[PDB]
Image 1: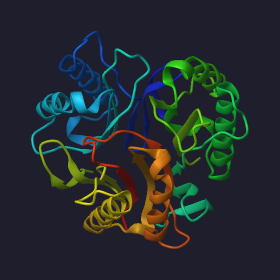
Image 2: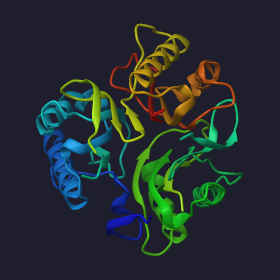
Image 3: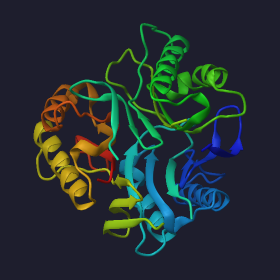
Length: 116
Length: 116
Length: 116
C-alpha cells in the first residue's frame, strides 16, 4: 500500500519500491574518467541497488541510458552493457544524448525493475 | 482493468491512471520567466494533478527532470525541489539536460506516482 | 511473477512484459528520411509491438518522445501523432530534444502500456 525507500536524501531516494516494482534514481559513475570505466561504475551501482531492493539484473524491466556524447560513446557503452547483462535476458532500453549534471559525467542510466 | 484519463486533448492526457499507478504528462511552467519561478509553477501543476488522480507528493515513485541548461540551473532547481518535497520522503529521480518545446521553457518534470 | 520478453538481442528486448504492464524499447524509424515519414514508421513499429505484447493503442499509459530538433520538427511530430492516436484516448506524454544514436534519426519514442 505504501512506497518504501532506500538511501534517501533531501533531493532523492536511490530506490523507491512500490508493490512489485522498483524505481531507481539515475545512477552516475564513480571516479572513472573514461567511458568504459564510467559505464562499469554506473552498472555496478545499479546492481547493488537492485540487490538492496529485492530485485536482480534478470528482472530489469526498462533502462534509459543517457550519454553526454552519443556519437562518441555509443559503441563503448554497448560493449560494457552487453557484457554486464545476463545472457539472453536483456531489458527494454532507450539510449539518447543528454548532458548530465557535471560535464565530466559521460553516462547515466535510469532503471525500473521487478521485485523478486 | 481499464486506464482512465484526466484532462485529455488531441495530443495527451495530463494524467493516466492504471490500477495503483498514476502517469503524469511532462509538466511545463506557467508564466514565470526565471528558473526559480518556473520550477515552482511546474511543481504546483504536478501537485494538483496528483490530487486529481488520487495520489499525493508523498506517493511519488519517480521524477525525470529536464533542464534546458543543466549547468546554469541545477542549483536553483534543487533549491525549489527540496523545499517542495515532503520531508524525508523524496522519490527516485533523474535530472538531465534537454531543450523543451519552447526556448523560453527552462524546466519540465515528468512524474509517476502511486494511487493512495 | 516473471518478466517475459519479445525480440531479445544482446543489447535489449523490443518489449518486456511484467504482470499487466508492457515496457517497450525506444522505437526508431525505418527507411524514411523526413520527419513525417520517420514518425509514421516509429509509430507503426510501436503498434506492432503493442499487438505482440497483448496491448493496443488505447492502452498506452505513457510516451516519451525524443526529437533531434524539437524546434524544427515538433509541429510535424504532433500532426502524425494526433492522427495515429485513437480518438479521445491520448496517453500521458513528454516531448523533449535529444540526439539519437544515428544523426539521420529525427525521432524516437518510448512507450509503456497496459496489458489487455
